[PDB]
Image (cartoon, rainbow, N blue to C red; front, side, top):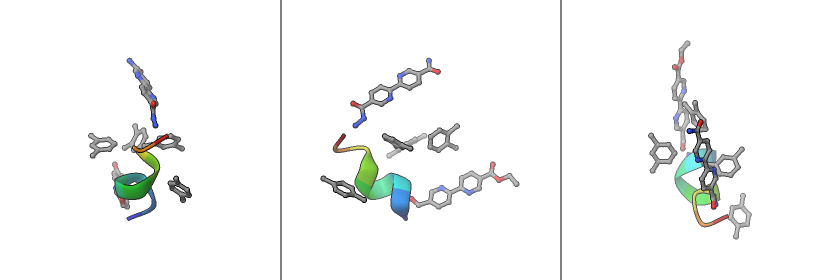
Length: 9
Ligand SMILES: *C(=O)c1ccc(-c2ccc(C(=O)OCC)cn2)nc1
Ligand SMILES: *NNC(=O)c1ccc(-c2ccc(C(N)=O)cn2)nc1
Ligand SMILES: Cc1ccc(C)cc1
Ligand SMILES: Cc1cccc(C)c1
Ligand SMILES: Cc1cccc(C)c1
Ligand SMILES: Cc1ccccc1C
């Protein structure tokens, strides 16, 4: 999950 969001950065 964290990665799914952090892809933005
Ligand atoms: C959420 O974006 C998220 C959570 C966890 C993972 C993930 C990817 C790969 C592994 C892995 O290779 O585990 C080997 C023990 C674990 N967790 N991706 C995305
Ligand atoms: N928000 N994330 C990024 O902007 C981002 C772009 C690209 C990468 C990355 C990481 C690792 C590799 C590699 N070939 O091992 C390539 N590109 N990380 C973050
Ligand atoms: C965990 C996280 C991912 C993306 C942004 C833009 C901020 C925090
Ligand atoms: C969406 C996404 C983020 C990070 C890494 C992978 C393979 C996919
Ligand atoms: C998918 C991803 C982007 C930026 C930083 C991290 C740790 C993960
Ligand atoms: C599985 C994974 C997730 C996020 C960043 C790098 C890697 C190897």
